Length: 60
DNA sequence: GCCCTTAGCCCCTTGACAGGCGGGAAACATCGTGTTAACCTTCGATTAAGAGTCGCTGAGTCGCGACG
Picture 1 (cartoon, rainbow, N blue to C red):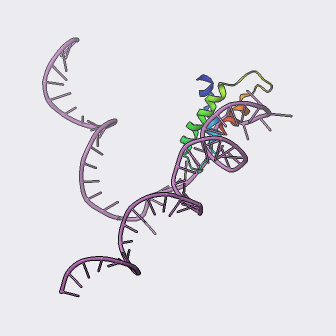
Picture 2: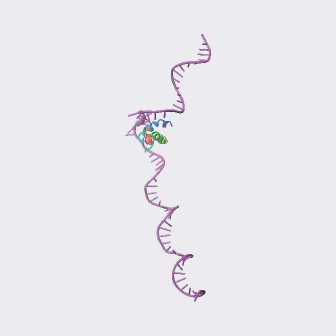
Picture 3: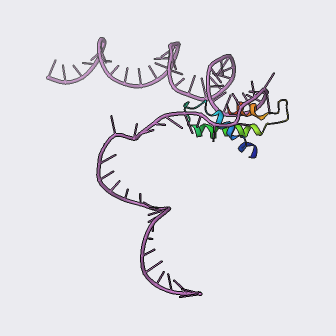
């Protein structure tokens, strides 16, 4: 939950390019939150430990 | 004029298909999942150039009195 709340701003930033695609902005954010929470379930110490890229891929 | 004999129509029995809904068996196009990890961790409209009224809130002005 801490990692999600400390990254939700990421989802907010990614949900700006999909605006006006059949879903509201907050709806898109709270839908991408599902993928974000699904990303933390599979997040190990692999190469490139930056969670930015992984989070943006899963929100997309 | 009535009875007998024979012909035509109606009805019954079988049947050789024809294919025809439909489940099965199969070959093939969906629909919900995952999974990848090289860089940005606040996006954006939209009234607001007429008009009669409902529902709430928060400032400045006064009484009643006590303690010197």
